[PDB]
Amino acid sequence: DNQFYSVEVGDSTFTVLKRYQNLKPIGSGAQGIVCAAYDAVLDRNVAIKKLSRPFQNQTHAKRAYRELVLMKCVNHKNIISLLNVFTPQKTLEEFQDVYLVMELMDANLCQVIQMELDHERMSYLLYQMLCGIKHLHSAGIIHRDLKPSNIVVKSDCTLKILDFGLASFMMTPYVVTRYYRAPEVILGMGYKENVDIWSVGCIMGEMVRHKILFPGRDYIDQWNKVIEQLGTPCPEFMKKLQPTVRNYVENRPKYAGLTFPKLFPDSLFPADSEHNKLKASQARDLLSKMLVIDPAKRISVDDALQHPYINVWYDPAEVEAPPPQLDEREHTIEEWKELIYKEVMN
Ligand SMILES: O=C(Nc1cnn(-c2csc(C(=O)NC3COC3)c2)c1)Nc1c(F)cccc1Cl
Image (tube, rainbow, N blue to C red; front, side, top):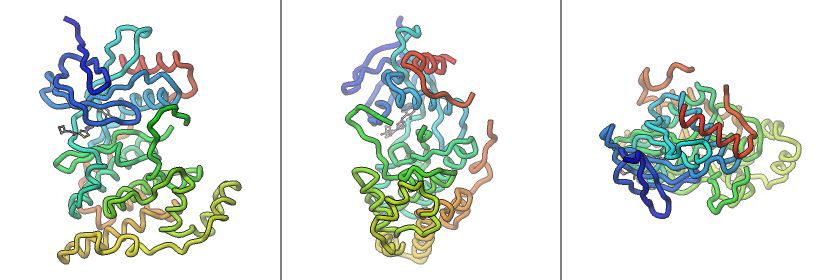
């Protein structure tokens, strides 16, 4: 007779609508735990995400509220869509957890990066990532924190981006992945649309090399990896850093930078035919236009899509889409709880 039922997925209690059956663990993100389930009404498999007390702190609250708001309006194949939103709690006072439902995907882009993919799959995943980013940009949303763990894929190579980016202190054991963040973000230096192009390049290079391009304990070790490989940036770029950050970066040892065939040799690409020899040079040309420290000289999202390696997948209804109280910040626990509760029940 009750509309919900309780099941223990590992060590996380999922209390869901009775339509959701056969829950199975499939991932453990920094925001919440996710399950696979069969939906009895839609007759299809779905993913369920639980947000445990999203209102418990500013970082948790601004992301939980912001994503619920942005999902209600963005409409694209390469951006996550919500099939459902629900809370087992009946009142604001008892309100604790929120559950988000989406189509069940088959794998995380982290899993896909470990595979030796051909040029056709590699170029189709990169194409979709750019279409998703271009739609977010079209809707006034520059991401700034795109990474493989918040990107999911189907067996038919279709791709969807799960989060919406940046808005500080998290008092937990799990630490955030900063390896795909642009130099503009690392150095706390103003941004524009192509900041996400850098993150696409970090993914593309890792797809080729099968290792994180810019590893590091903190942004100190990270900036070391960006200049050792790509070189110390030109004086034009140093002439737009903040004074304090400028003296750090200009004081760092200078590097000429390894050329893109040295960083990504012919060995790492399929080269068994003329078609593959050409596609290796086209992929290496794009990596060299995406992994550019200066955003003024880094490639556009529109130009990235029109590049020969990517423009083989172009279609009119898979690039642009008709665009449409723009978010809130700084609230108590109770004020954030109420704002999030409002979005959950319209
Ligand atoms: O991760 C999330 N979603 C997601 C969708 N597919 N997947 C997935 C990754 S691996 C995998 C798998 O193994 N599928 C097998 C093939 O049949 C089982 C499946 C993960 N978060 C999320 C959510 F769940 C709900 C709403 C918002 C968000 Cl953001």
